[PDB]
Length: 316
Ligand SMILES: [Mn+2]
Ligand SMILES: [Mn+2]
Ligand SMILES: [Mn+2]
Image (cartoon, rainbow, N blue to C red):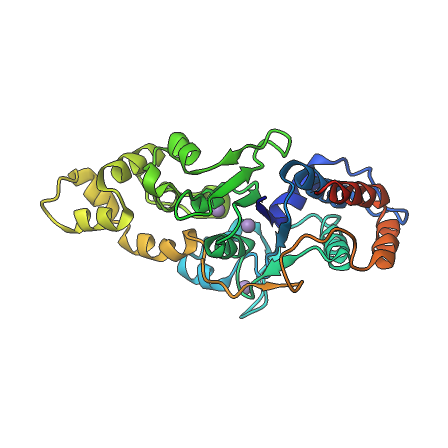
């Protein structure tokens, strides 16, 4: 049985856009994201039958240490920047933010493991927990393709990304083979190589311009030929490497961006993760059944909690 690691914010944003906003609590507040997010857990529990499951939090969705390296990072998504230490106010619809609070309440009362690392993103939590796992195959559940950098075959246990780009129902599991087949990175280091390719090609939806003149195809063939990004910069710095002069000029005109983006684009694998629960075991019933029942009533997702309990009951 795999341990599921859930990219919480990716998922309840998906649920917010995948469940109609006319699904409301008795007090009138939309709870479409809450319903959608709980149902996704039940769907995941029934499909994967995990014993262990963690909802990974964004203690800081936009850490200033990444913004100091690449100021444009996630900048088009900031509602209001907050100074030193305080996470920036993300641009989020006014009727989704209370729903995030509802979800965290329901998880806390149920006792579903959540995890976070102060000053780090959920993606770092995901990378840390998947890097450290030594017992069970890891399924990272997310709509964020950046996480494909976590895929792993060996050393065991394997790590797959159950990718939500087309929704949960169509989601398949991505491993090094799929990543290699889809982006042209070498299979023996598909995960890390994917992150090196994303650095070079850029990622506009996160405000990372990438290296001008080096698209994804060119990035792949330079990894397919030089094996690793460190090698590409050496081949560029060494004046008679086989590198084309055009490619050298593009790479040298970007050395400081390449260096600064390295730690921005790669997820941290050694973040100080803390759990809300003593362990990452999935509980088979609510830790606080009365509060769960009260919060679900108040939040208008009683039937979703009902369906979660049935999925849990069907675990062997
Ligand atoms: Mn800030
Ligand atoms: Mn994220
Ligand atoms: Mn990204």
